[PDB]
Amino acid sequence: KVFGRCELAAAMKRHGLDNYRGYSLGNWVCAAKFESNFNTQATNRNTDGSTDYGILQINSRWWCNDGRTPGSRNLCNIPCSALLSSDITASVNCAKKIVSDGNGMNAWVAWRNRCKGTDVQAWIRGCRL
Ligand SMILES: [Cl-]
Ligand SMILES: [Cl-]
Ligand SMILES: [Cl-]
Ligand SMILES: [Cl-]
Ligand SMILES: [Cl-]
Ligand SMILES: [Cl-]
Ligand code: NA
């Protein structure tokens, strides 16, 4: 599923991301825009052989099992395919774990490079929330 901006903001709000570890909802919607273009089906291979999955591009090195990333962990205890669902529950629940790990939203390269320090409230402007 390719979300609209506000549709994703509502879905993220309802699943408890708004202000989660102190990151306002705009930061999550901004991260999703630049990680996946709001596409739950997005996948991208990394050089190390891991793959990033879903609307928030969660990596199989640490967070999910894809059966082809040797010596990786699955800290979210999910198949990576779960992160591609049109239902973002798995993605959000795994994102909560990531963001809690110590490095905050710096775990998302696109957030650090394109969202951090920017006017992220722009991403939820006009939305009914
Ligand atoms: Cl929308
Ligand atoms: Cl915000
Ligand atoms: Cl992989
Ligand atoms: Cl699994
Ligand atoms: Cl959802
Ligand atoms: Cl933080
Ligand atoms: Na893994």
Image (cartoon, rainbow, N blue to C red):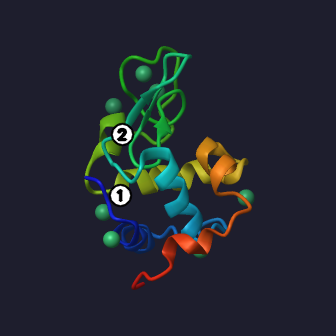
State the image coordinates of residue 111 (x, y, percent, origin top left).
62, 51
Above/below status of 67 relative to 120 = above
Residue drawn at the location 50% of the way across and 79% of the way down: 125
Crowd tier of the residue under label 2, counting other residues whose Cα lies within 10 Å: few below 14, some 14–19, many 20 or above: some
Q: Amino acid at mark 2?
A: Ala
The C terminus, quarter of image:
bottom left
Crowd tier of the residue under label 1, counting other residues whose Cα lies within 10 Å: few below 14, some 14–19, many 20 or above: some
State the image coordinates of residue 63 (x, y, percent, origin top left).
50, 36
Above/below status of 70 relative to 24 = above
Please identify, in this view, whether the residue under mark 2 or under mark 1 is nearer the observer.
2
Q: Secondary structure at mark 2?
A: loop
Residue 25 occupies quadrant: bottom right
Above/below status of 7 relative to 78 = below
Front-most of 82 and 73? Answer: 82
State the image coordinates of residue 29 (x, y, percent, origin top left).
49, 62
Left or right? Give the position of 9 relative to 120. Answer: left
State the image coordinates of residue 116 (x, y, percent, origin top left).
70, 57
Q: Which residue is mark 2?
A: 42
Front-most of 118 and 92? Answer: 118
Q: Which residue is mark 1?
A: 89
* Ligand 1 image-quadrant field: bottom left
Residue drawn at the location 47% of the way across and 54% of the way down: 33
Residue 121 occupies quadrant: bottom right
